[PDB]
Image (cartoon, grey):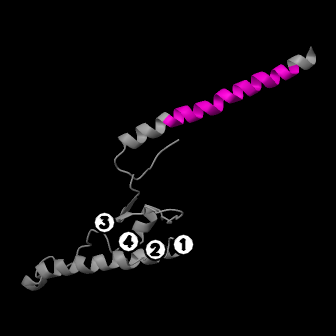
């Protein structure tokens, strides 16, 4: 719903990245909060440093018909979050239903 | 006779060209199926 398929009738490469940023970024929002909820006690007496959470997003780019969603390089997409995710090698895996 | 053999060139060359293209379809018919069945990581759709 969030996309409403604004890519289906138009070019996609430029804004597709823009689309996932809001999705990947908010995942990290709850990634730290749940860590924070469990680390509220002890007032971070030990291990005060905040570890980089792990994020994995499973996207299927199946196109209904006459549509070509643009898919970015996995590695290049992943490393864009260097310093926010531990698994910089891969943060999203793109697959098409067979 | 020279004309006949000169177009014999074309016949054999055309014949040989017919065998090369079709095999790429056959072999490629077989290769795509095994790779799709065997690979499970899914980061590569198929190879030709």
Helix, strand or loop under label 1: loop
Q: Earlier in the sequence, mark 4 or mark 3?
A: 3
Q: Is residue A86 left or right of residue A97?
A: left
Q: Over which residues does the magenta segment extend?
A: B6-29
Q: CA distance from mark 1 to mark 4?
A: 32 Å
| Residue that numbered label 2 is attached to | A5
Other residues around mark 1 within 10 Å, as few (<14) / some (14–19) / many (≥20)? few
| Residue that numbered label 1 is attached to | A9
Q: Considering depth in this image, is B30 or A85 the residue closer to the camera?
A: B30
| Residue that numbered label 4 is attached to | A82
Q: Earlier in the sequence, mark 3 or mark 2?
A: 2
Q: Position of residue A98 (x, y in %)?
A: 39, 51
Tag 2–tag 1 contact (CB < 8 Å): yes
The quadrant holding residue A53 is bottom left
> On what subunit does the disc labeled 1 rest?
A
Helix, strand or loop under label 3: loop
Residue pictured at 10% horizontal, 82% vertical? A45
The quadrant holding residue B21 is top right
| Residue that numbered label 3 is attached to | A56
| Mark 2 on the same chain as mark 1 | yes
Provide the major secondary structure of the magenta segment: helix
Q: Is residue A70 magenta?
A: no
């Amino acid at each position: 719903k969030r996309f409403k398929g604004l890519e289906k009738k138009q070019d996609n490469r430029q804004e597709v990245t823009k689309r996932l940023m809001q999705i990947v970024e908010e995942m990290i929002a709850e990634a730290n909060e749940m860590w924070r909820s469990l680390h509220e006690d002890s007032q971070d007496d030990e291990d005060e440093e905040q570890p980089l959470p792990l994020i994995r997003l499973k996207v299927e780019y199946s196109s209904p018909e006459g549509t070509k969603f643009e898919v970015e390089n996995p590695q290049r997409f992943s490393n864009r979050f260097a310093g926010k995710v531990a698994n910089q090698n891969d943060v999203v895996h793109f697959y098409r239903k067979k | 006779a020279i004309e006949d053999l000169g177009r014999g060139m074309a016949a054999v060359d055309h014949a040989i060209m017919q065998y090369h293209s079709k095999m790429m379809e056959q072999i490629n018919r077989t290769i795509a199926e095994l790779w799709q069945s065997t690979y499970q990581g899914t980061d590569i759709d198929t190879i030709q």
